[PDB]
DNA sequence: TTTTTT
């Protein structure tokens, strides 16, 4: 009776909710928290005891009576609620930061946006300013990794766009590759991003690319649920022998809003994908099969500034893989680990988000960077497909080797082989030409652009 | 004794039932629910407390006595009643909608049809009309994905019949393949379907078609129990080196009314197959064994419209696999995610059902669409 | 009970069943044939009936 | 008991 009344006033505050996945989220310390192995509901009961009248607060000091109140609470929670539906809100440990504005909400204002994830650190408005003498050093670091030159113009913009999208709690349709040689600043960029978003950043394994995602317990993919930034590192030169290729099957799966995969000792097979997936590379990736659906999901950022020791500087100024060579800063790595640039980089990310990802958040691919897509890109501009616009032109097509078969358009295999040998040699694309012939095999409905 | 009379009175209202599989289904808030990891019987005991007499209601406020009532109820439940025997009913969170007429039943009327699953959302009879601009916008979306042209007439009809089959809860004799190239609208159709039926829609992994099911817990199979639509997206290019060529025996099991599979920490191994299984494909399927039984189990719906960007428009118009080229809507996935077209696509599905699947529901195969079946 | 190309080429789904059916024989694994004869492998109570489309070849 | 292991 008395412990039933206490449980009712707790649900009157809407401080505990039931989610569609069966989790009980609680509102403690200005944040929605959930944990499958922690007593969070009884934690809320003890914390909320100050907002109760005098006769009710004294009965919440007994752990046994807090379990009775908790048992009452779980019986009254019959309907689920939707959580994490605002993509333009950045949730901290003590509130939610609006990204369309610079406003910070802490209290009942941040409760409306049921963000069950958070960075894990309290937001500091005294460091989220602009001037911030650490911000000068951060500008020095960023302007070295991605120089502000005319040559590094579209690459710098892509770099800013990709890092900014890690603040958006929506589904991202592209996978970005951080490509560069050694000592170029990719790991520095990763460590700066991890310092700025905290627990919203997760580091995952290499399986999520090169193996099936649903073959039993796969914690390496179930840990990406509601994470806004996923990093994979150091693909082991898949173009060489003894390697498993990228398996473009997973590339399309990782783009979908829902990724199938379950943790250990649980049946939750659906995870929500809000993550910008970035892979650090020293070599360009190679895929098992190249498809137009694969070239629509790949972007590449190039790192071309080398940070070297004074001894081996001259060996780096004569390398074609570097555009600039700079002194390595030995204390920079330890300063990032101490979250010195935690809020300056966050201010940078918010500014870039306002510049790029408003009002529509979307990541666009760069097919012209991957060498594996060169054949498909060339064929896309080399051939016209079938018919309809060419039937009246067949009078002029009697010459130039064009013949008629099946009454649409045809080309003999030998004719097409000889013609395609005149645009690019088979030294590097011989297997590619053979694969195209086999996949589109005899007659070939394809017309050259110059013969129109 | 008093807690035994409370349990008997609760049992007299037929709000707790036992299923042949072993589930305990409760009637809370105009919907049958079952869950093996949630105190659903105690939730009903607390909620039903307003219908019991005055002296019996105070005894139900103590949690410890509610587990006593629950134990009494679980001991009383010896019989077992069949569930989900109406294939033309759409269960919502606040009632059941008839798919033959337009009547919506809420309350004790919806209780007769023991629909243990639900869409998960409430039925709002304000957008379920035909009018309002959501329908006009949606009809443009559908008419661009599958144009009303005469050459697409049979394909458009097969598209309508397959989607409307997700409304009917029964065993479907065909597995439909959604075939098309990139930016053809297959995932848009899937996302429209998910918002329309909600919890009656589940996505499963690739092991339901390529891997032997009988090993340990199989949540990817146990989650298809009573679901009316199962999507398995991203069919890989098995016609290459190092791949698994689906499985012809799985299709036989996936067409059977009973599917074997158990969850984690659970003994329930029988699942009822009520789902229209659709696979999102950029490549048409191949199989290890091509039998005669496999012939009447596969249907193919082809998407031939490209939603390109202004930059890459000229190249798209010179492609064989595209019949029309349109403009991609950047702010359309957000509208679908916010469930804007939830009750308009639902009305479209209901109309297609009334036109196609009454009074007989059946799906026909299209083997003259796969190169393998030609021989 | 119905089962295809698994038992010949489900231990729980063979117990006390009075009949077990196998279909469309796609060798036949005579070692598996000898196993189903013994009462204990669960207990065998099923007249395991096979229907074929073409004349089968043993190993 | 599931996972781990086969
Ligand atoms: N702006 C900078 N000025 C000076 N040193 C820097 C700067 N940015 C990064 N460094 C340092 O340069 C070193 C190499 O950078 P690092 O982050 O390791 O790039 P990397 O690409 O991950 N190396 P690798 O893994 O071989 O590709 C580290 O010790 C960094 O602390
Ligand atoms: N009728 C439409 N009008 C405008 N844009 C549309 C329409 N239908 C779909 N789109 C958009 O077109 C894009 C591609 O659609 P999508 O659902 O991804 O097709 P898809 O075939 O599944 N992609 P893929 O996996 O490569 O085959 C998405 O951004 C959709 O929002
Ligand atoms: Mg590194
Ligand atoms: Mg898709």
Image (cartoon, coloured by chain):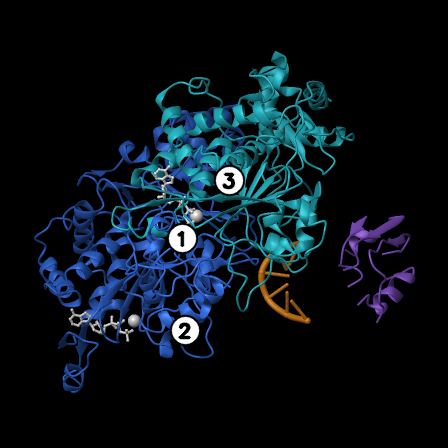
Chain colours: A blue, B cyan, C purple, D orange
B90 lies left or right of C5: left
- Give the mark toward the camera: 3 or 1: 1
State the image coordinates of residue A121 (x, y, percent, origin top left).
28, 51
Q: Is mark 2 within 8 Å of ligand 1?
A: no
Using the numbered discs, state the Cα–Cα distance from disc 2 to disc 3 in whole angstroms.
41 Å
Name the residue that disc number 3 marks: A22
Find residue A379 and report its image quarter.
Answer: bottom left
Quadrant housing the C terminus of chain B: bottom right
Q: Nearer the viewer, residue B184 or A265?
A: B184
Name the residue that disc number 2 marks: A238
The mark nearer the N terminus, 2 or 3, is 3
A198 lies left or right of A153: right
> Quadrant holding ligand 1?
bottom left
Tag 2 secondary structure: loop
**Could one spot residue B55 in this view of the protein?**
yes
- Mark 3, chain letter? A
Q: Which mark is residue A132?
A: none
B188 lies left or right of B169: left
Using the numbered discs, state the Cα–Cα distance from disc 3 to disc 1 in whole angstroms.
54 Å
**Callout 3 crowding tier (Cα within 10 Å): few <14, some 14–19, many ≥20:** few
**Could one spot residue B93 in this view of the protein?**
no
Name the residue that disc number 1 marks: A386
């Amino acid at each position: 009776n008395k412990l039933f009344n206490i449980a009712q006033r707790i649900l009157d505050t809407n401080s505990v909710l039931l989610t569609e996945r069966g989790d009980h989220i609680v509102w403690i310390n200005n944040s929605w928290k959930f944990n499958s192995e922690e007593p969070l509901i009884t934690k809320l009961i003890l914390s909320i005891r100050h907002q109760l009248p005098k006769e009710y607060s004294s009965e919440l000091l007994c752990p046994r009576k807090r379990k009775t109140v908790e048992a009452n609470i779980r019986d009254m929670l019959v309907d689920s609620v939707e959580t994490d539906t605002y993509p333009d809100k950045l949730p901290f440990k003590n509130g939610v930061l609006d990204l369309v504005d610079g406003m910070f909400y802490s209290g009942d204002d941040a409760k409306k946006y049921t963000c069950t994830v958070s960075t894990g650190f309290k937001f500091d408005d005294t460091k989220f300013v602009e001037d911030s003498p650490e911000m000068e050093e951060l500008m020095n670091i960023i302007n070295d990794i991605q120089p502000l030159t005319d040559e590094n113009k579209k690459n710098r913009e892509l770099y800013e766009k990709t890092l900014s999208s890690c603040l958006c709690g929506a589904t991202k349709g592209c996978l970005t590759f951080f490509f560069g040689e050694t000592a170029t600043g990719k790991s520095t960029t990763k460590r700066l991003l991890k310092s700025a978003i905290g627990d919203l950043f997760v580091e995952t394994g290499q399986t999520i690319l090169t193996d099936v995602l649903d073959k039993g317990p796969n914690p390496f993919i179930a840990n990406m649920h509601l994470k806004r930034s996923v990093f994979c590192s150091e693909l082991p030169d898949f173009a060489c022998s003894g390697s498993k290729k990228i398996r473009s099957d997973n590339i399309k799966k990782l783009t979908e809003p829902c990724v199938i995969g379950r943790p250990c000792f649980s049946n939750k097979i659906n995870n929500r994908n809000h993550a910008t997936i970035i892979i650090d590379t020293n070599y360009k990736p190679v895929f098992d099969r190249i498809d137009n659906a694969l070239m629509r999901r790949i972007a590449v950022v190039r790192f071309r500034t080398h940070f070297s020791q004074p001894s081996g500087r001259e060996a780096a100024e004569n390398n074609d893989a570097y555009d600039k060579v700079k002194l390595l800063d030995e204390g920079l790595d330890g300063k990032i680990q101490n979250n010195r640039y935690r809020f300056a980089f966050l201010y940078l990310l918010v500014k870039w988000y306002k510049k790029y990802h408003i009002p529509i958040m979307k990541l666009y691919p760069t097919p012209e960077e991957i060498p594996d897509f060169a054949f498909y890109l060339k064929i896309g501009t080399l051939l016209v497909s079938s018919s309809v616009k060419h039937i009246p032109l067949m009078t002029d097509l009697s010459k130039k080797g064009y013949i008629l078969y099946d009454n649409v358009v045809t080309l003999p295999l030998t004719t097409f082989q000889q013609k395609i040998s005149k645009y690019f040699n088979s030294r590097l694309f011989g297997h590619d030409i053979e694969s195209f012939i086999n996949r589109h095999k005899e007659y070939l409905q394809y017309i050259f652009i110059e013969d129109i």
